[PDB]
Amino acid sequence: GSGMLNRVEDILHELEGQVEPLKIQASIAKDYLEKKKELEHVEIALTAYDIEELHGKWSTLKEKVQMAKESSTLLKDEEVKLGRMEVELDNLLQYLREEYSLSFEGAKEKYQLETDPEEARKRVKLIKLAIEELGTVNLGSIDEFERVNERYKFLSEQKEDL
Amino acid sequence: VEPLKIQASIAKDYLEKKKELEHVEIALTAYDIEELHGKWSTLKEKVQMAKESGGSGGSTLLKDEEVKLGRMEVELDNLLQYLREEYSLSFEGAKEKYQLETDPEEARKRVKLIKLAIEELGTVNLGSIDEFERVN
């Protein structure tokens, strides 16, 4: 014979059971990735905003401290504040590199706030909560669903010759 | 034993992607440092000539550029810190060891893609490589 003993119905039944479950996980995973994308966009914009704002404040204060010197406890208090700003500024800049591989210029160019920063920060919290409420996410299910579904479709729509 | 092979293959794929990620991240950092330093050099020169043109006193446009010049310096310093702290590298070390294979913007897209592919592997057990090599 030129035919096959194994019926395609068997593999189809084995796969059909797998389609819908993977579809659910994949739909959850895509939703997660969408919220993650939104979160990242807002966080990059906030980071660039905070860097420019904080550097501006630190620059100004550092100039006033140095201007006053050239002219004791009060002075020390300002220097402590300068130190705190410097640590925070360094952290923000290094965060930009480590988390996004973006320069400040690159971040600002592509992502700027479209609301006041506090509104953006609240938005960040709300997106994080939404992500958290998705529970356990299986990212691999997106690719796994694609493979299983395409295979199932291939065999289904051509079962007559399989 | 087969559930091990799966686990071990995942672990090795994880290691390979992390190497891939590191190379593009450091290559970009070295590239960005040199580009930023060039922009800083260009702007600093431009600031100087403005003070020579005269009448720039109290100019808010000149002040904006001076603040920008300062922010560039702080960013450069922090990029150098990042190389030291994260990879124990100097700028020249990073540049010489890690060269971009593509244009910078495509590399930036690649960074996010590799990170996602890594995250897609889920929880990785590196020790599965060991107990797999043990079954043989």
Image (tube, coloured by chain):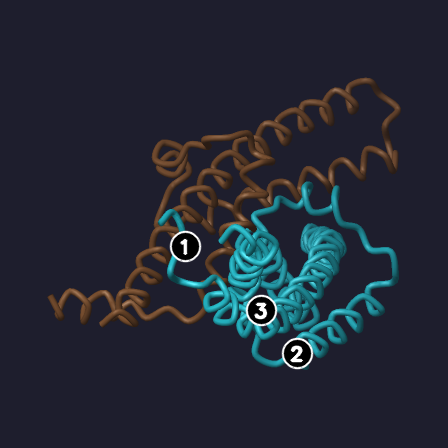
Chain colours: A cyan, B brown
Chain of residue at mark 3: A
Q: Can the viewer see residue A63?
A: yes
Q: Residue at x 38, y 60 (%)?
A: A5
Q: Nearer the viewer, residue B94 or A143?
A: A143
Q: Position of residue A118 (x, y in %)?
A: 83, 69
Q: Are marks 3 and 1 on the same chain?
A: no
Residues marked 2 and 3, same chain: yes
Q: Is residue A43 left or right of residue A138?
A: right
Of A123 and B17, nearer the camera is: B17
Secondary structure, mark 1, is: helix
B98 to the left or right of A85: left
- Residue B129 point in image, percent of width and height: 23, 65
Graded by Cα atoms within 10 Å as few (under 14), some (14 to 19) or many (20 or more), the crowding at tag 1 reads: few
- Identify which residue is drawn at 87% across, 38% down: B60
Q: Which mark is residue B86?
A: 1
Which residue reaches farthest front? A1
Q: What amino acid type should be assigned to the residue bearing mark 3?
A: Val
Task: Look at the image and tell me whether residue A60 can be seen.
Answer: no
On residue B58, which mark appears? none
Cα distance, mark 2 to mark 3?
Answer: 21 Å
Q: Secondary structure at mark 3?
A: helix
Q: Amino acid at mark 2?
A: Leu
Task: Identify the residue position indicated by label 3 in the image.
Answer: A19
| Tally of marks | 3
First along the sequence among labels 2 and 3: 3
Does the residue at mark 2 contact the one at mark 1 (Cβ under 8 Å)? Answer: no
A147 to the left or right of B8: right
The quadrant holding residue B73 is: top right
Residue labelled with disc 2: A134
